[PDB]
Amino acid sequence: STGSATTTPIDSLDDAYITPVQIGTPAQTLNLDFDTGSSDLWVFSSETTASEVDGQTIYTPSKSTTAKLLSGATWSISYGDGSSSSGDVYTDTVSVGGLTVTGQAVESAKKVSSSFTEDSTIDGLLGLAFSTLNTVSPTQQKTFFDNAKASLDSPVFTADLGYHAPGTYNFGFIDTTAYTGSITYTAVSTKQGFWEWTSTGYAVGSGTFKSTSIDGIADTGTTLLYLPATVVSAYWAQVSGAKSSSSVGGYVFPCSATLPSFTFGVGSARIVIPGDYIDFGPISTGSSSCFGGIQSSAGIGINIFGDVALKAAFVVFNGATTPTLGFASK
Image 1 (cartoon, rainbow, N blue to C red):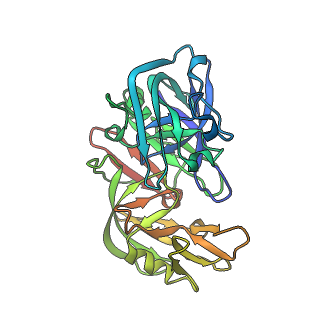
Image 2 (image 1 turned 180 degrees about the vertical axis):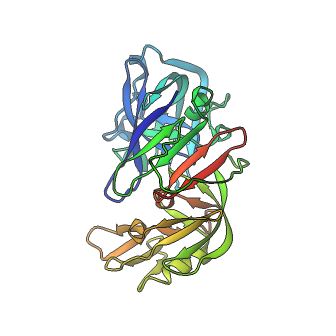
């Protein structure tokens, strides 16, 4: 089997991407944030505290003839950005772009934190990291990809995120028309439950490539590119007027600037992030100070190749017995 679904930016800044997902019988379509940095599939639902719902589409398990309460199971998750959610668990039929899993754990939110309530465009998350990170207790549950894997033509999924435009998630096949050149594969450690790999270095604009190992995660659920302070300083040093602002919480730059590109290494290959991908617009409405798309990972504890990086590439998440990651230009 295979599946293919279009993924769409939630806003003009590509703050996140949503992908339609069919849940239950008859289908209830929710727009979920596919997140390779976590491993829970959770949804706004008929069980979510009413005051915490503000425009999201909800899953109502009582209206699904295939929904079954998973007895005694609960979940609770806290993300790197301080947001959180929790609730109970159903199993139900879940389909993505034509690919169907029966008995998928669908984690129904009873509580969500303010940032979720405040974002009417995201109806939940679909985790695509390794199932070892799944928070369901007392019996850990598998991700959608883990459940689908054996049935797929090839045990892979691909992320092809657009810049200010739609893109595609494919399951079970590699669309050879979706990228240029070849796909360079690189080793993955699953030891922390993430798609964790080591970049071979970086360049800023037309500058010389610096060979240096950067361990990080491929995370479609993080908006920006978080890298070591030395790397980030080298980037923003090339932008007149850019500075790290403690009050704003990162590097800001004059909105009038033209940003340089940023290149990262995948083996001997190179992925070039155009400067425009690094502009996240005014810090507040009407401001001429703009937020940077490359930020320090210091105090996160891990480097994160988030959407800013991933959207410059066609990315293969290879779930073979020994997982690997593949990157191609596009």
